[PDB]
Image (cartoon, rainbow, N blue to C red; front, side):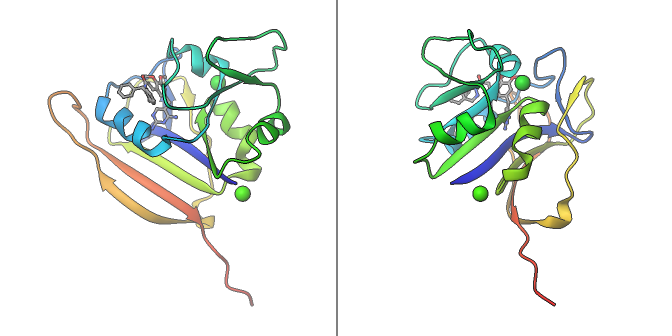
Length: 166
Ligand SMILES: COc1cc(Cc2cnc(N)nc2N)cc(/C=C/C(=O)N2N=Cc3ccccc3[C@@H]2c2ccccc2)c1OC
Ligand SMILES: [Ca+2]
Ligand SMILES: [Cl-]
């Protein structure tokens, strides 16, 4: 099972402002949709609510410690272990964010899908630091910038850098 972080952050790792995206890049979200199609999406409650709805064609799994938390059209999981069991037969799952949610899955991550937005926004929550010497880029592509997607941004994908033995 490939454990993948899915993330869009600015030049200071901002991933949110007052629980919402400080940017509006529909093309970027079209990319998330295309990339995650047919795979589970894993996200925290706060993250999930910051959207209002669930993405069709995707297994939405909400992670909260709240044992009474339910939402229609979604699954709820209360620990890392419960998510892995639930996703036991899946080839790839996408950790869809919450800083804390990313942190929960750090010891397990195999793949990084990182959108980097070339701008500094006002933010209050951040993509956790990561030592990238352990990682190797396998794909990059400049996003579509135009009237609907004002900012300049790049899709990046990283896999684990294999170490060559001494
Ligand atoms: C705080 O608000 C958000 C945060 C995140 C987290 C996130 C976004 N992008 C990337 N690359 N990584 C992330 N972890 C998503 C979202 C996603 C928003 C959102 O509305 N969508 N994001 C993806 C998606 C996937 C399947 C069905 C529908 C959607 C939907 C969408 C909207 C417009 C065009 C195409 C698809 C979000 O809401 C705006
Ligand atoms: Ca793995
Ligand atoms: Cl969250």
